[PDB]
Amino acid sequence: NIESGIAHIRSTFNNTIVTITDTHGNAISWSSAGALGFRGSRKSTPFAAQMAAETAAKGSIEHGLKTLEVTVKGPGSGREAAIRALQAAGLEVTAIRDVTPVPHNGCRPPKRRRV
RNA sequence: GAACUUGAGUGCAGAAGAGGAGAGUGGAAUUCCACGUGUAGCGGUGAAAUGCGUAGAGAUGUGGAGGAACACCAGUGGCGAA
Image 1: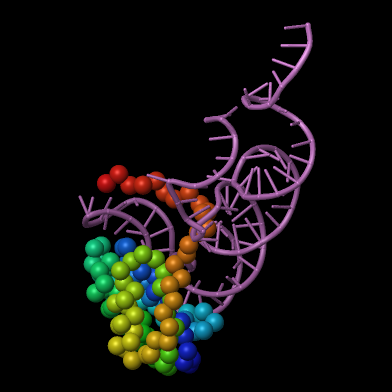
Image 2: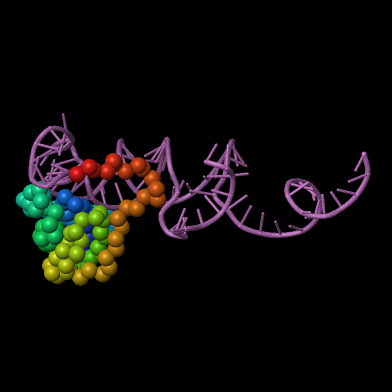
């Protein structure tokens, strides 16, 4: 039973995962578009991000959270939907923080697609 | 052969620079390894599948290993014969 937590939203182009943890990063609960039965294109859509956030939130509310800090990673379109969905579940969102990993010129990226 | 100082160079006084070689050091990120929390998918596509995952993955926290490259600055900006 913990109150304050961080909501890690990993929004990629293919899927949106939402893990909810305590302030010390111990996992309370998590949800992802795939876990909710979305497949392929559907998982990417922002609608699925909403549903993923709601499902993750309702799992956490059992443990008794009230305030969430939000961290967003990846280039997906889910972050806004997932954040608004967390607010709609009742948990107040203190601050959103983009923590997408930025290399300072490190590893060579994979070759560009010729689509 | 003898003069001259503009070319060329030297002296003296300043200026900028990713110019080069050598030796160190630093932060981000990817991967891997160990551990805590935690559960059913993760990944990928135009759509899928191969692949990875209940032998506990992906997500998340701490620490560690190693290799390569140096975000912002950064600019028809600088330096170099290329």
